[PDB]
Image: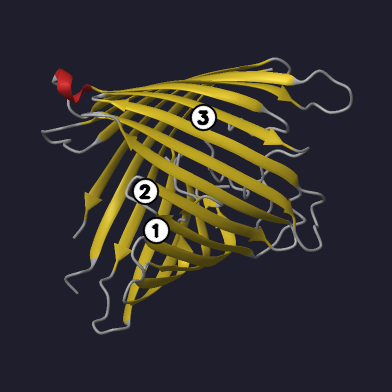
Amino acid sequence: LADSSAHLDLRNFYQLRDYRQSQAGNWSQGFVLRLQSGFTGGPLGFGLDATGLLGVKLPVDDYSHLGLTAKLRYSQTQLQVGILMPQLPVAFRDDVRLLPQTFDGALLTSSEIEGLTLTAGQLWKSRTRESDDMYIMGRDKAHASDEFNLAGATYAFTPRLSASYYYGQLKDIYRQHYLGLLHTLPLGEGLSLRSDLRYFDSGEDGAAISGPVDNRNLNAMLTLRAGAHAFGIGVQKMIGNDAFPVLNGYTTPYVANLMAYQTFTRPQEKSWQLRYDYDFAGLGLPGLNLMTRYVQGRDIDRGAGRADDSEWERNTDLSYVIQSGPLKSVALKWRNITYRSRYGADLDENRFIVNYTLKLW
């Protein structure tokens, strides 16, 4: 049993919001207990993981759940059945709040052939700190489905160039095709251009119990890395009459212009991003990083014959991984969020998040 391990992930989360068309605060604490067995010896290996989740309001117990995950392994192929945290282009579980969003399902991954990863899965339920079954975020939770089917392939053509295709199907609600092209171009010592191009095509599926689904999503992130600096531009475009479909539960839309508050995927929205990163290591402060980014959106469809909405958001994050002493490896994050829109809400918000992972064995 020496290959087994246990960890406890701790998250302390404080947010001060000023939302209006009101200054309210929130302090809370997350625990994620991860138990992972090793694998039963032999060609076909067997294992068992357990994931325990607890959210506490700051103290009153707010949310708890315990899930198990059976795992099988053979050569380069793995099957997991039970609690899952998928991080896939058509289902990228949320983890920017207190606790990670989880799913129950079965996920098969296989990397038998050099440079090729194949994925096939089915998710049956979504769980968040807030009566299950899945639906498009923003639509009728009464017209839900217990079956999300996914299949994918990623191929590294060269170590500079890889491509990905994924298919997501929420049975009887929607279908989604994803195409991604990732190109990294070296440009001299400490220099590289990362081109991250993404395309989603979303339509209805089966009985279409939540109504029509019409969205194509074109988005790209170009990132110039230079020594300890990084400079990025993002462009994103919603086409069709619908917002970009994601699974309910604040699942993260896998998109270039995703921000701390808004996703910039509203119906017909066109947006661009500027982002700057700095690693302070060279300056003598390893573990300290600055990220600041700004996204501006327009042409947001408000229907009828109304004027389109428009919006902007700025995010500034200062993050610090403590390098030594009793709190070594404790991570701190200060996030400043500023958001304005023409016809909707305005927001100012500060968050302070402390993360730490304790190894139990």
Q: Is residue 339 left or right of residue 354?
A: right
**Cα–Cα gap, marks 3 and 1:** 28 Å
> Residue at the spot x=53%, y=66% of the render?
121
Q: Which residue is mark 2?
A: 31
The foreground one among 52 and 252 is: 252
Percent x, y of residue 262: 58, 29
Percent x, y of residue 268: 72, 31
N-term-proximal mark, 3 vs 2: 2
- Residue type beneath disc 1: Gly
Find out whether the residues at labels 3 and 2 contact each other: C-beta distance under 8 Å: no
> Residue at the spot x=46%, y=38% of the render?
196
Above or below — where is 272 with respect to 37?
above
Q: Is residue 334 left or right of residue 96?
A: left
The quadrant in which residue 189 appears is top left
Mark 2 surroundings within 10 Å by alpha-carbon count, few (fewer than 14), some (14 through 19), many (20 or more)? many
Q: Which residue is mark 3?
A: 259
**Cα–Cα gap, marks 3 and 2:** 25 Å
The foreground one among 266 and 230 is: 230
Find out whether the residues at labels 2 and 1 contact each other: C-beta distance under 8 Å: yes
- Residue type beneath disc 3: Met
Q: Is residue 128 visible?
A: no
Mark 1 surroundings within 10 Å by alpha-carbon count, few (fewer than 14), some (14 through 19), many (20 or more)? some
Q: Secondary structure at mark 3?
A: loop
N-term-proximal mark, 2 vs 1: 2
N-term-proximal mark, 3 vs 1: 1
The quadrant in which residue 132 appears is bottom right
Q: Which residue is mark 1?
A: 52
> Residue at the spot x=56%, y=49% of the render?
179
